[PDB]
Length: 292
Length: 9
Image 1 (cartoon, rainbow over the protein chains, first blue to last red):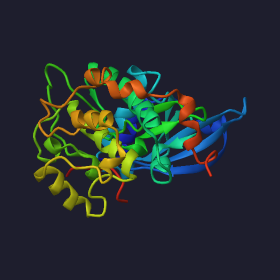
Image 2: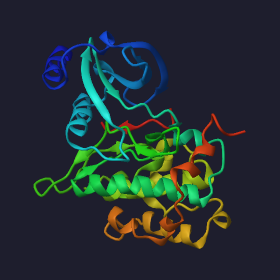
Image 3: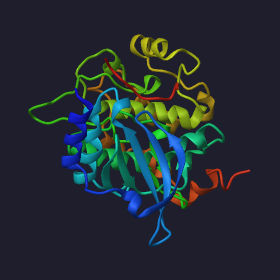
């Protein structure tokens, strides 16, 4: 449990050195559950990278910090943020990664309305990432708009893998209470063993974000909302009259209480709602630097 | 911090 013991363990798996030897002008842009995110300038090129900083002493489960290393080493994809290097800097784990200059989807859903071409484009991109992760046994466990980042030209990428877990023939299900209350699958709140299906439920909640601006029960305390997710029928759109029958049918395959009956990522890639998906260009006008 | 991830006890 010793802090210095965990520092030593992390040193054996990260890259050697200190990225301050090649980065300038750190500017904090976000705060997450495990640390902060900064932009930095590569001194040699003038290019911008992102740097995630996580204090080992502030982690509820320090061992989840290895998730950043496992994902960086073994899982790369068009719709997953690319991670370049990891370092131990003092008491902090620093991950130098791709900078997604378009910011997070949260800023869009809380400030503007997406049309279904844009919603389908986000869902297709997320589902392509999840289909590849799930096929290799990786569960993200924190799908929500805050975890979805954008490039300046509207490309959509999944980020924040600090909470993921792996399943396999020898470990078929996970049991840990991990996620963000309003987005958690009911079987996970019920403390039942769960699998990749919980990301599909969370994606459904994110679809409700994209239509309503906020997840269900967001006005309720997080523990109250979890009880309602667990005990009540699947949450409803507040604006059901504002979604096409195609979107509603899509959402109906995501927000299924029985995880055996929930659609998988591979199945959802074939759903007709995703035929509405626009190109990344259709997402560009939603971002702060472009909207009015 | 309503949007923050939680990790069970």
